[PDB]
Amino acid sequence: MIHLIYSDQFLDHGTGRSHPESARRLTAIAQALKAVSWANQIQWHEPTAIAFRDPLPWVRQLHDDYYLKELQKLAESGGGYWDPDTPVSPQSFDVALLAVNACLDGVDLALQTKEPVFALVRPPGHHATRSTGMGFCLLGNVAIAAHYALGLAGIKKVAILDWDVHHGNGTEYLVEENPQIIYCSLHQDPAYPGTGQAHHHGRHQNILNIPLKPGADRRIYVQKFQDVVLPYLQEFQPDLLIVSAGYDATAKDPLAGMNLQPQDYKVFSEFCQQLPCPILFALEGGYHLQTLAESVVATLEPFAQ
Ligand SMILES: [Zn+2]
């Protein structure tokens, strides 16, 4: 059984006509997951409404009250642009709180069932910092979910693995100070947002940045996974793995310069299965629609058998 957490309200985060972070990204994925041979093994879940679980007691662990206030106020005044690349529609604050709630649900569900969970959310989260949204990101979904998980019985350690093509500067900033969390990122260098050097390990030796030259494909990523990533995660022995699952390191993705194929994410998930803990995937980037759908399918296929 594979758990998908999805609401059509995630489609209501409005980014504009030709913005690459589009609502269709979700439809494209959903259609593919419903078309696959093992579709009857997917259980769909609607995320907990924010009227029932207010996520702010966890959002506020990470983000400034001033930032939260200003974001909500931009949304409720009719929308706008937080920066040139990061639109906010009237629904966007509520939609981002629901995306947090979907990840919180995913933590709950992964812990309860020991089965994989994919939070099919917009907006993405891994660039959002304590005090501002950026790079299409409003709130730090995965870092917030990790902090939520640490409040739960049986979770004393969380590992985050970010395979979005871009460094998760927000995630890193938000979890670096926390000895209960480790963060591992594989990312293109040079690429947006110009952060993550390999020598930055945080004061807790809990940050492992793996920058890679443009043009990387399956071979170099698999080498890093077997030689660097899984030894690091395994020595820490986390009670939960949260994967920032972005799919923009693919050859066909328009925003970046790596050359992965959809089927490579199957290998990445197989590596992650070597860990004994449960796994929550949370959608980040990935912008070519067909490639993105095929890549989510590949990500979850190793769990179908
Ligand atoms: Zn990205």
Image: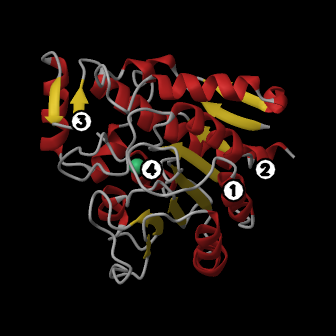
Looking at the picture, which amino acid does disc 4 mark?
A: Val
Q: Is residue 133 above or below residue 62?
A: above
Residue 11: x %, y % from top left: 43, 20
State yes or no: discs 3 and 1 in contact (Cβ < 8 Å): no
- The circle on residue 302 is 2
User: Reading the chain from its start, which is encountered first: label 4 or label 3?
Assistant: 3
Looking at the picture, which amino acid does disc 3 mark?
A: Thr
- Spatial separation of the CA atoms under disc 1 and disc 4: 17 Å
State yes or no: discs 2 and 1 in contact (Cβ < 8 Å): yes
Q: Is residue 131 above or below residue 226?
A: above
* Residue at mark 1: 269
- Spatial separation of the CA atoms under disc 4 and disc 3: 19 Å
Decide if residue 48 is in sight here.
Answer: no
- Left or right? Give the position of 113 relative to 280: right
Residue 178 occupies quadrant = bottom left
The residue sitting at the right extreme is: 305
Q: Is residue 108 above or below residue 48?
A: below
User: Which mark is in front, 4 or 3?
Assistant: 3
- The circle on residue 86 is 3
* Residue at mark 4: 142
